[PDB]
Length: 20
Length: 20
Figure 1: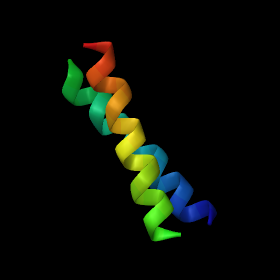
Figure 2: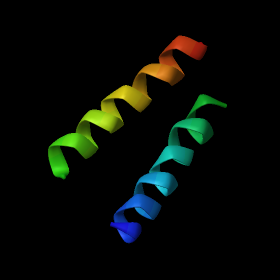
Figure 3: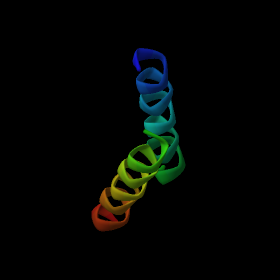
């Protein structure tokens, strides 16, 4: 569970990077 | 797990659209 949670957290930053 | 992860992804997608 922790690895996929970290992967989802990493994917979360993609939308923040694309918003700029 | 995958279905609820996709649901969380779809919910996350709404916050960036609401922020704009």
